[PDB]
Figure 1: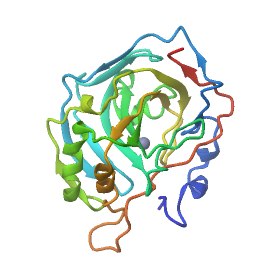
Figure 2 (figure 1 turned 135 degrees about the vertical axis):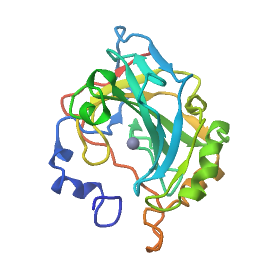
Figure 3 (figure 1 turned 180 degrees about the vertical axis):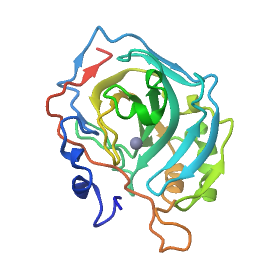
Figure 4 (figure 1 turned 45 degrees about the vertical axis):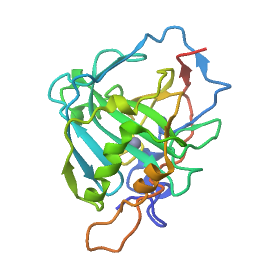
Length: 257
Ligand SMILES: [Zn+2]
């Protein structure tokens, strides 16, 4: 049902998913003039050395690069987090134009795309249980701008032809998500939600300040994906982003001065 089209986009989601109008919805605009440095944040720890990618899937809204999350292979800890969060998948949101595509915004600026590395809190045993908890997930968000190519993204780009349409998957082993990180791990953090239905308010968001650069050709290949299934009318998978939601009774904290 829901999507990013003319008649089922974000402004409609509340009908089936009333938390869309909830108190802790994501994404949000990050106002760098009101986010306050929090000296209590602990150091943030990205431990991806043992990550095991498995597969890439076009799910009809984005594509997910999936990982083995049956052991502590690729974990996020530190920062605002208590305990250990295991990487389950990453995916992106992107635009039809280089001036839009991100979900979070920074002083109202939209980036060309946004990467979400999704992790679940191991204290809840599995992802499906974790999403029912306010501290169930930690999502590392990374902005993409168009400029230089990102060499560590090219393996993703090159497999997209094999998953053009909804429901297609491909083997995708030995991919290193460290190749998608910027140099700095400085971040903003706030409590929020999944940005797609069911929009559950289970996420500690960790949004990196430093964007990564991807080339025009890399983003153009994202924009060749399809929302539709094979044999259905072609609808390019573009503008698969939810706009900023009201901050309400939340504060955004910065890890850096
Ligand atoms: Zn996302």
